[PDB]
Length: 525
Ligand SMILES: [Zn+2]
Ligand SMILES: [Zn+2]
Image (cartoon, rainbow, N blue to C red):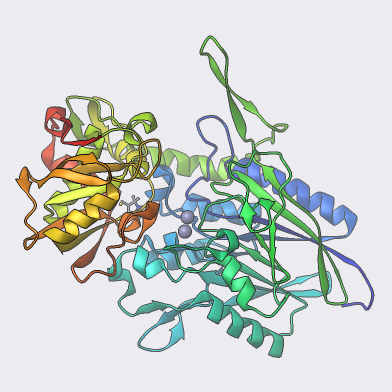
């Protein structure tokens, strides 16, 4: 670079896109509006003599039925048009076989990076560790890192000869390699690890904060995050804002001279970090999260509702609409499949699933027990994302109930472990995502103790073995649930939640909702 010259570099970033190539039903986000917003920033920055780098934190896959059944092709092709420069591989990039991810690398005109994923038998990386970019006369290196929880979280069949090494140890080696060979002026890490307040990861694998602390001071200009699905806006030192408002200022986190940013999810925001480079120094001038046609739900006293833009409308780029429309129609044609029927509504509403036992909880858990041969089951009410109306059931309806690509697991445990496990789970309160939905369990919860506890209408025998079904999420500590993944009787089946529910509905159709009707088997006080 030129000695003493001040350079302008804008880093644009998104993460956890999760199939949101199209605007939602309220006209929010979508890649068409993202394209207009990004095009306008490129033009403004170019007129100032600056540079733009557009990065993704990964998890493009899974989350919208139209996208899922097309293996995120519209998302990857849309990202080429927005003009993404690099992407970190996320854990949801492993929801599909490795061959599908290879085809996503063919569709993407930008590299999909991960330095820490290795073939066990050969000791070779499966992906490119980093990519290099020339911006003005500056050399910028982008490193990709994936959470080492991936194999633990996903389908085990996909990881037999694959290992996810500790991303922080891998980042140290990659930084040192780059400093010794390519000598970039700027190093950025695009990651899919998550942001945890003060590095308090809990049951999750260590994330961004912990990694930034372990690295040499300021060795990375920034960590472009993802995974945790949070707008990284600090309320105080080592504390992110709870319930961040779109359009408000966003103070990103800084740990050991390294900025840590995240742009929430679903293309809702484009994060913008404006930096100035001079003589090796990188200084952040401004940081913002730009809403992408986000709308506030406004409810009048007469009960009438409307959705209103927080900021002025971003027009949808027509070239993006022409690219995406055929995939939106193809996605719909693929979703036009009747998988079964129900004689009644299956209650999946938030104000029900997080408060009381519902027939949708019983249906999902019946599907999970049937696939695993389980005696009983439990799941977080927060894992039930929609209802199924009376009548015909489409694959789309099933995907809306279970949209996250969770995996079905089971654990064989003693009656004593069953007693201890259900006692801790019964402590989860209503009005929370952690509120438990049970199947084949009955008790009267009183003073943190379970009375008349039964499995399949029978008292729990401590010596007896019982199989419980749940999701990978809960089994690994999700929502503060007791860990099952470290128990000897644990088995991760690899089966997706939506596929298990779909197939069970198919073979049990027509559903008689009376069979799934909760009758106060579990109660508190
Ligand atoms: Zn993730
Ligand atoms: Zn995610």
